[PDB]
Image (tube, rainbow, N blue to C red; front, side):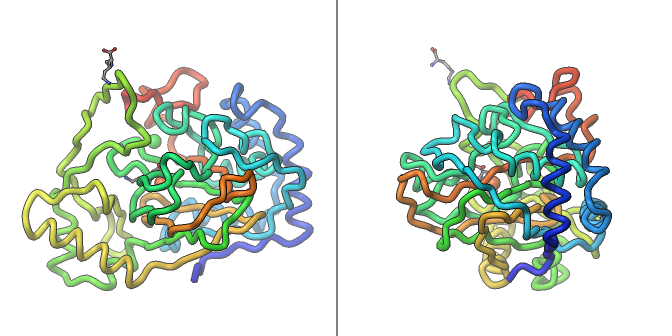
Length: 325
Ligand SMILES: N[C@@H](CCCC[NH3+])C(=O)O
Ligand SMILES: N[C@@H](CCCC[NH3+])C(=O)O
Ligand SMILES: [Cl-]
Ligand SMILES: [Fe+2]
């Protein structure tokens, strides 16, 4: 279903593989040096690839996402971890290919409250949180959402590199432009009004953790920005309308999503960039085995402007402190 596709040629993938050798710093323990090295090395990538990523990063009339095919094959992948605490993806050659493409688009960032602030987070099924609304779920559909809908420091892009896929695990994508095309002028206007409260994601909460902005946030609008290139903040599960029409309108958005969403099954060697301002995403049910061969994605986050989170970070740090989310 996915429209915006970048297919790397054999020669382009070989250049990416060679350029990755310029990124030598430890992704977890020297995250800033690692990301700065990727940003500099990204200048050595094929110009056709860099041009595509820069136009996607600018954002104007982009499709809400970019699917990249043809990344070099990951040859000695360790078993899929049964939890996200290990940060296994951050060691692989794919993580350096992911950083190179990411740093073309913008600045990599991590959040202390999400996957322990790991530069790359392991997106693997959990047996305990199989029926939960998190990146580690599987038995239930991961409902429609903006990544960190509750946070003003939410990423500009979500980067997903596939290490192991699952044929039943579909990624759903739905743009703010697809939404607006199905709505009336009145519905678009109400969506632009501050009528919905949000709460902090389950994955962000912890014992003794206090957020400067609280647990409950808003009311905020769902839509914003230009009429022809709208921005979206949505959370199917956690948004609550402040009025009866606002609640009905949240259901209208969900219905438009089920009717118009595009799907894609992430496969090894593929990378998906989601524009977190222009598109919302979801994930179907799948049946993991927890045998070490399950679906395994490497997730990272990108921001255009590192100065917006400077108050929340340490000097030469890539991690936003939990209380600032
Ligand atoms: N972004 C969440 C999943 C969506 C939850 C939406 N309230 C996670 O990584 O766990
Ligand atoms: N359970 C903690 C309090 C932490 C705050 C609630 N998450 C205690 O030892 O009193
Ligand atoms: Cl930010
Ligand atoms: Fe998510």
